Structure formats: structure tokens, C-alpha cells
Image (cartoon, grey):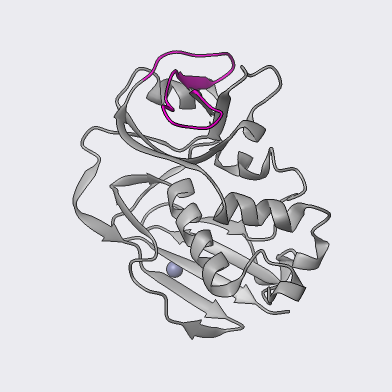
Amino acid sequence: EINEKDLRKKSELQGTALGNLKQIYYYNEKAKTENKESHDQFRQHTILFKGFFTDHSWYNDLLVRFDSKDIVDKYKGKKVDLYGAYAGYQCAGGTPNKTACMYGGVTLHDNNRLTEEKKVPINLWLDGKQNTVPLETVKTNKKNVTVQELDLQARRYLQEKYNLYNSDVFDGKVQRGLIVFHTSTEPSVNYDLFGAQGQYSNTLLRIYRDNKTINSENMHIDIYLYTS
Ligand SMILES: [Zn+2]
């Protein structure tokens, strides 16, 4: 859905934007658990996992937020697996004290586990030159996987290897970047790595609120990074 000349420059990011992006993709807290269920709803298009956290320094409950009633209805009252980044700062006003919020991150549990862990191949280009990416960098045990699960893993590696969301003074050389989740069937999801209004940490991950899921079978990821 995006061409390279239309990629947003890192220099456009205002204020706390880079710091927020680095936190959400490299210093995050993730819910990663299997075979859970809830049909408790707070309001809106949400599933509330009461007492999800037993040893968190602030949270007791996890609130999952979705875009629509059709999406929440797919998962409400079903055995699901979770894989997403949560935080209190992701909640809308009036969410209960000690509740943390995640956007999407849910998949049906049943019949979704692969027998062999899927290593998702990555094609990465930096200023047009291919760079080798370890095959274990992005992996999943799910047949139907959230784009969130794959994007969190890919961007954590981009921060570690290329200092993606570091300032220019802290060796963050990449100025533009695109990630594509290239499926066998289905138009591919693509995200501009510098496309968000990063200064609003509460909505940074609202892109995942659609709970988009894709088939991992035979898929791969393409990453295009530019230093200008
Ligand atoms: Zn591709």
C-alpha cells in the first residue's frame, strides 16, 4: 500500500516520538500466554481478563481493545492465545485503576498450533543492499498469527541491530523504513516504520486494534531501510 518515495522521514518526528517508539518496540511489556478465555466486557469492543496478572507491580487486569463488534465477537468466550504489548497508557479514560490495555493481539487457540515452529524468513535491504538476517529472528507457533506478533519481533531486531529508534546522535542512522508482511494469498500488510505520530504513546499501537491476522504458511517479511 506504500511506495518508497512516500515514506515519512525520521526528521519529521516531533518531541517524544522517537523515545515513545523505542519504548514500545524495545522496552515493552508483553502478554504472551496460551489457552485463556473471557467473556467479561468492560464497555465498547473489549475483552477483560480479570486477574490476568499475578506478579505485576501495578496491574491486576488486562483489557483487550478491538476496533469493532464483529472483531470482538470472534474471540469473546472462546479459547484464545495472546501476544501483544500492554500498558496502562494504552487505556481510554475511565478504565479501572490497575487495569492495563492491549490493542488486539488475540488468536483462536484451537487447531492453531504448528507442530514445527515457523521461522519467518526476512528479506532486508539497507540502502538497496541485502543484509543477512538470522532465520530465528521472527518466529511463531501459530498458523493464523497477528501482524502484531510478527511486527513486535521484527522491530525489536531492527532496534537491536540498526538502532532504529535511537536519535541521530546515538547512532540511529536509518531515516526511512518500510516493513511488509508478504503473504501467499491476500494483499500484504505494510507499515511505514516512521509513519506514526509517535508523540502520542497512547495511540502508537492503535494500528494493531484491528487484530489483523494472517496465515504464516509460506509467508515472509520484507524490510527496506534507507539512511537518507
Ligand atoms: Zn516479499
**Residue 113 shown in magenta:** no
Residue furthest to the left in view is 115
Tell me what residue is drawn at x 48 percent, y 32 percent. 56
The answer, for residue 219, to whether it is visible in the render is yes
| Residue 197, above or below 57 | below
Dominant secondary structure, magenta? loop
Tell me what residue is drawn at x 65 percent, y 77 percent. 226
Q: What is the total number of numbered labels drawn onto the structure image?
A: 0
Tell me what residue is drawn at x 49 percent, y 83 percent. 130
**Residue 43 shown in magenta:** yes
| Residue 77, above or below 215 | above
| Residue 165, above or below 76 | below
Picture coordinates of residue 186, whole percent (x, y): 42, 52
The N terminus lies in quadrant: bottom right
Image quadrant of ligand 1 equals bottom left
For residue 200, which quarter of the picture? top right
Picture coordinates of residue 213, whole percent (x, y): 42, 43
The C terminus lies in quadrant: bottom right
Picture coordinates of residue 87, whole percent (x, y): 59, 36
Residue furthest to the bottom in view is 129
For residue 33, which quarter of the picture? top left
Picture coordinates of residue 132, whole percent (x, y): 42, 81
Tell me what residue is drawn at x 63 percent, y 52 percent. 23
Q: Which residues are magenta?
A: 38-60
The answer, for residue 9, to whether it is visible in the render is no
| Residue 209, above or below 150 | above
